[PDB]
Each structure stands twice: as C-alpha cells, then as structure tokens.
Image: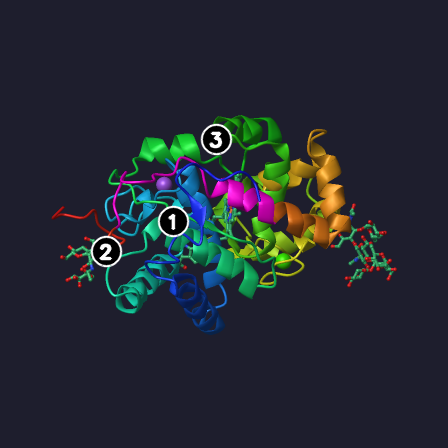
Amino acid sequence: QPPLAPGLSFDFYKRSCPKAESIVRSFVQDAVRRDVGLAAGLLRLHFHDCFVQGCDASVLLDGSATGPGEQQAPPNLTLRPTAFKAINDIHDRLHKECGGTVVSCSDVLALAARDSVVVSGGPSYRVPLGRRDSASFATQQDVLSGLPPPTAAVPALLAVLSKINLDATDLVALSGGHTIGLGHCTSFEDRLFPRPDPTLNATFAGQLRRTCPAKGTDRRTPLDVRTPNAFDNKYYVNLVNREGLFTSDQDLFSNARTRALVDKFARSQRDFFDQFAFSVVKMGQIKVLTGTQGQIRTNCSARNAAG
Ligand SMILES: *[C@@H]1O[C@H](CO)[C@@H](O[C@@H]2O[C@H](CO)[C@@H](O[C@@H]3O[C@H](CO)[C@@H](O)[C@H](O[C@H]4O[C@H](CO)[C@@H](O)[C@H](O)[C@@H]4O)[C@@H]3O[C@@H]3OC[C@@H](O)[C@H](O)[C@H]3O)[C@H](O)[C@H]2NC(C)=O)[C@H](O[C@@H]2O[C@@H](C)[C@@H](O)[C@@H](O)[C@@H]2O)[C@H]1NC(C)=O
Ligand code: HEM
Ligand SMILES: *[C@@H]1O[C@H](CO)[C@@H](O[C@@H]2O[C@H](CO)[C@@H](O)[C@H](O)[C@H]2NC(C)=O)[C@H](O[C@@H]2O[C@@H](C)[C@@H](O)[C@@H](O)[C@@H]2O)[C@H]1NC(C)=O
Ligand SMILES: O=C(O)Cc1c[nH]c2ccccc12
Ligand SMILES: [Ca+2]
Ligand code: NA
C-alpha cells in the first residue's frame, strides 16, 4: 500500500462492526448482477467525491452541487442516479447489521468502489477505513475547481492532480477507471464536429459519428470500445490504437510525460492492476476527516441534525 493518512487504519471496524466490509461486498455483488453499469457508477462516485473537496462524502448531500438533488448540471456532471441510491441502501443495511449507525458514508464509498472493481474482474486490494463525513455542501466552484474536464490535456490534468498530491503515474493508472462505464456524446463531440480531431483513429471517428451524428446528441456510449463492462487493461489497448474516447484519455498516449506508462499498461494487465490498486488507495485518502472531525451520517443524503 501507499502510506496511510493519519487517523485511518485497515479493518477500522474490527470491534465496532466486524461484518461491515462483508456486508458491502455482498450488496454490491447482488446489485451489479441486476444492473451491470452500477459498478462503473460506484467507482466514479468515489473518484468524483474525492476530487470535490476531499474523500468526505460531500457530494452525497442533497444540496451539494452534482449531488442527488442536482437538476441544473450538464450531462457530464450529472452522475448515475442508481449509484446514489446504492450507497444509501448499503448504509441502511449496515444500520441493521451493525446494530446502529457505525460506518461512515465516506467509508462506504471507498469500499463500494473496491467491490465494484473486483466484481468487474479487477484487482482486490485492502481499503483503509476511519473516514468521517463532511458537513459542508459542495458548491459549483468546488466542483469546477476540483474536477478537470474531458477537454483537458496532460499538463492541465497534472496541475490539478499536483494540488492533491497525485503524480503522472497516478494519472495514467487512475484514468484506467475508464475501462468500464459510459460517456455522454457531449463530453467528446468537439472531437467530431466540425471536423474530426486528427488524434482520433479515423475508423473509430466514423463509428462514433453514428453514435453521435451531431452536436447535442443526448446519448451515452462505452468509455472502453473493446470491453465496456470488464475491468481490464483494454482501456490502454484503445489508447495505443488512438481510440481513447476523451481528449483527456488519448492525450495520455500523446504527451511525453505519460506515454511510456500507457505502453507499459497496454502490454501488461498485471502491471496496470498493481499500479491501479496502489493509486486508487492513495486517491481515496485525499483530505479525509478523521477522529472526531465530521460526522457519521445517519442518512448519507443529509447532515446530522440532532448532534
Ligand atoms: C485504428 O483502429 C483500428 C480498429 O478500429 C485498428 O485496426 C486493428 O488493428 C489491430 C492491431 O492493432 C488488428 O489486430 C491484429 O490483427 C492481426 C491480424 O489478424 C493479429 O495477428 C494481431 O494479433 C497479434 O498482435 C496483438 C497485439 O496487437 C496481440 O495481442 C496478439 O496476441 C497477436 O500477437 C491483432 O489481433 C488482435 O489481437 C488481440 C485480440 O484481442 C483481438 O481480437 C485481435 O483482433 C485488427 O485486426 C485491426 N482491425 C481493423 C478493423 O482493421 C488500427 O490499427 C492499424 O491499422 C490496422 C489495419 C493494422 O494495420 C494495424 O496493425 C494498425 O495498427 C488503428 N489505427 C491506428 C493504430 O493507427
Ligand atoms: C482525472 C481525470 C478524469 C477526467 C477528465 C474524467 C472525466 C470523465 C468524464 C467526462 C466522464 C463521463 C461523464 C459523462 O459524459 O456522462 C467520466 C466517467 C467515468 N469516470 Fe472519469 N475522469 C477522470 C478520472 C477518473 C478516475 C480517477 C476514475 C476512477 C478511478 C474515473 C472513473 C470514471 C467512471 C467509472 C466513469 C463512468 C461512470 C458511469 O458510467 O456511471 N474517472 N470520467
Ligand atoms: C435522507 O435525506 C434525504 C435528504 O434530505 C431525504 O430526501 C428528501 O426528502 C425531502 C422530504 O422530506 C424532499 O423534500 C427532498 O426532495 C428529498 N431529497 C431527495 C434527493 O430525495 C430522505 O427522505 C426520504 O426520501 C424522500 C424521497 C421522501 O420520501 C422522504 O419522506 C423520505 O423520508 C432521507 N431518507 C430518510 C430515510 O430519512
Ligand atoms: O440516463 C440517465 O439519464 C441516467 C444517468 C445520469 N447520468 C448517468 C451516467 C451514466 C449512466 C447513466 C446516467
Ligand atoms: Ca474494459
Ligand atoms: Na467530497
């Protein structure tokens, strides 16, 4: 593992709810079997939360920008509704199984993301626990400052990541999250219209134009054209074929700082999986609340209102 943030530990709930991790995994395994895309939704939700203020469940709050109440966001800042619901359903199950409110929503996010990776065929890894839940709503400015757009090139991505102490190795490995899940036409339409972006494989560009025949097409397509739902290194095989979906994907292969790692991971899924496991655990410790800071929410969608 990477270093543990102060206040976090492996198996934090060993005494207070030893079954907690097992309960989350069982729920995710069943839920994803019914709704395959939920795994991508849960992984994304953990990333997104971490990049918006810190890994503190701020984005779960009804009232947070990009939260479950959000009606005034663009398609690519409108997160999958089933993933918000799954976190709450898991947290409800934990209330019953733990004998009360014990496990933070922030910890559920980190666990559910790991279980999503695993059920999709990805690597298992230990998740540090002990996070606590923010009582601050995320604002639009928090979202816009924290999250790079898919139009961003590597230097801009690295600048954002450096503020949260992630480097180019983490960028390339973590971007492999796009080995599962969906993207909206509007996140990549500028690469098609008016003319095709020269960095896009021309054969793929032709296929995407059926998928998104004009700007403003309200449709989603897999991030990974090779294996949409399997967690694997095919994301990187796409890049080396110039078939990354977003600018922020394909620039990983273009840019001198990141190209070697893209090649490495396209050639070795084991190398990708090892680095992903390290980097995603690093990501999930960004600006965490620990000790008595923050709350253990009784309802992941609301701040606790009675102490
Ligand atoms: C723009 O996108 C196109 C797809 O939309 C690319 O076309 C594809 O290119 C790939 C190679 O990159 C072709 O697949 C290969 O086909 C040959 C002949 O059948 C196989 O021998 C070869 O398998 C070997 O190499 C693999 C690594 O590349 C190894 O993993 C494998 O074990 C073998 O050692 C390979 O076959 C693929 O192997 C992996 C399997 O999972 C997969 O199912 C199998 O297909 C592919 O046939 C081709 N498809 C199309 C529709 O043309 C295109 O690539 C460029 O253009 C093509 C025509 C070829 O000249 C490529 O060599 C070339 O890179 C890409 N344009 C880019 C990359 O600029
Ligand atoms: C840091 C640079 C990143 C950028 C620019 C980026 C951008 C985006 C965009 C634009 C989408 C599609 C949204 C849409 O159009 O609806 C998305 C989806 C997704 N991203 Fe990222 N991403 C980044 C990093 C990450 C990381 C670090 C992970 C996880 C490790 C991740 C996992 C996902 C997943 C799984 C989806 C699909 C969600 C779904 O299907 O519900 N991304 N990404
Ligand atoms: C958990 O907190 C949520 C956020 O406060 C509650 O959701 C909401 O309830 C309000 C009605 O009291 C409503 O105005 C908001 O629109 C809504 N927000 C969202 C995103 O749904 C939620 O309460 C429940 O579920 C909603 C849909 C209603 O049926 C309520 O009567 C339910 O209590 C809270 N969940 C629980 C179990 O308390
Ligand atoms: O199809 C919808 O409207 C639900 C939705 C919102 N954002 C999403 C991201 C990925 C998959 C589905 C959705
Ligand atoms: Ca895949
Ligand atoms: Na957050």
Rendered image coloring scheme: rainbow
Q: Disc 1 marks which amino acid?
A: Thr
1 or 2: mark nearer the eye: 2
Residue position for label 1: 78
Whether the residue carrying mark 1 lies under 8 Å from ligand 4 is answered with yes
Left-right relation of 101 to 37: left
Q: Quadrant of the N terminus?
A: top right
1 or 3: mark nearer the eye: 3
Magenta segment boundaries in residue numbering: 277-296
**Earlier sequence position, callout 1 versus callout 3:** 1
Residue position for label 2: 299
- Determine the CA span between mark 1 and mark 2: 21 Å
Q: Quadrant of residue 6?
A: top left
Query: Please, is residue 106 above or below residue 230 in the view?
Result: above
Whether the residue carrying mark 2 lies under 8 Å from ligand 3 is answered with yes
**Earlier sequence position, callout 1 versus callout 2:** 1
* Most common SS among magenta residues: loop
Q: Disc 2 marks which amino acid?
A: Asn
Q: Residues within 10 Å of mark 3 (few under 14, many from 20)?
A: some
**Ligand number 1: quarter of image:** bottom right
Q: Secondary structure at mark 3?
A: loop
Which residue: 53% across, 49% down?
Answer: 214
Q: Secondary structure at mark 2?
A: loop
Residue 215 lies in the magenta stretch: no
Q: Quadrant of residue 77?
A: top left
**Mark seen at residue 164:** 3
